Amino acid sequence: PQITLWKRPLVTIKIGGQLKEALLDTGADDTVLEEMNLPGRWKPKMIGGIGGFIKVRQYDQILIEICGHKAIGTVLVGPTPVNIIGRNLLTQIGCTLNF
Amino acid sequence: PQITLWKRPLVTIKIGGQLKEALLDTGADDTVLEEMNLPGRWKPKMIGGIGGFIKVRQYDQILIEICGHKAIGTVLVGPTPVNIIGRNLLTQIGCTLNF
Ligand SMILES: CCC(CC)CN(C[C@@H](O)[C@H](Cc1ccccc1)NC(=O)O[C@H]1CO[C@H]2OCC[C@H]21)S(=O)(=O)c1ccc([C@@H](O)CO)cc1
């Protein structure tokens, strides 16, 4: 589909057997999801934005479905105020910017 | 153009007669640029991101050309980690997400 930007580009995602709303975010290198208790090993990471850094848990090879499009890659889990689909997964669903 | 997302969507902007690099950021409501001198009146404002809130100067109705496309809108100046172009201007240049 084509998503205009009059409002936040929120879409439904499926991750860890749960459905969530998340931003398709070209400004994020990686995908950052609100606190959730995923199984498996993880590595500590810190990511910086407006306001400073937050601590997140980096999980690798996680399957995410975005609007019925399947992807697999890294997801960072931490106290983000919003679920963020980053470029690491946006490329896997064929997402481009167009103007 | 059509912009793929294997690399950061960085583009050249012109604002206040000066060229700069900026990130096209669909996860940003607003456009926030790093500290710079801009002519005209401004008002102190706050904006929040993934790490908390910062103080910015709000410049309204500013002329800004993004990758050859003109916009006139609000520009917030403050300690953002990166120059970002947000939806308030992305809509003006006709930018959409497509997949
Ligand atoms: C380019 C640097 C920053 C942005 C300065 C990139 N961020 C994405 C950005 O889309 C962010 C998303 C967002 C966060 C909180 C609330 C709502 C949206 N939007 C944002 O701050 O918008 C501001 C401006 O407009 C307002 O609307 C929304 C808030 C206001 S991030 O989340 O901090 C981040 C940092 C590092 C990584 C790692 O992967 C390495 O990249 C991934 C993601």
Image: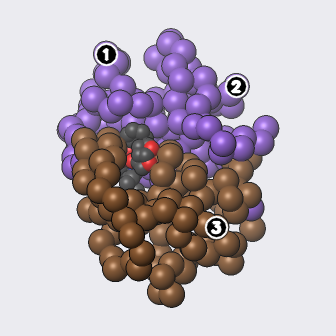
Chain colours: A purple, B brown
Front position in the image: A76 or A23? A23
Badge 3: residue crowd in 10 Å (few <14, some 14–19, many ≥20): some
Parent chain of label 1: A
Q: What label sits on residue B71 in the rendered view?
A: 3
Q: Residue furthest right?
A: A1
Vertical placement of B79 versus A76: above or below?
Answer: below
Label 3 to label 2, Cα distance in Å?
34 Å
Residue at the image position 31 percent from the left and 36 percent from the top: A58
Mark 3 residue type: Ala
Q: What label sits on residue A29 in the rendered view?
A: none
Per the image, the residue denoted by label 2 is A68
Q: Are marks 3 and 2 in contact (CB under 8 Å)?
A: no
Mark 2 residue type: Gly
Vertical placement of B40 versus B78: above or below?
Answer: below
Tag 2's secondary structure?
A: loop
Tag 3's secondary structure?
A: strand
Mark 1 residue type: Asn
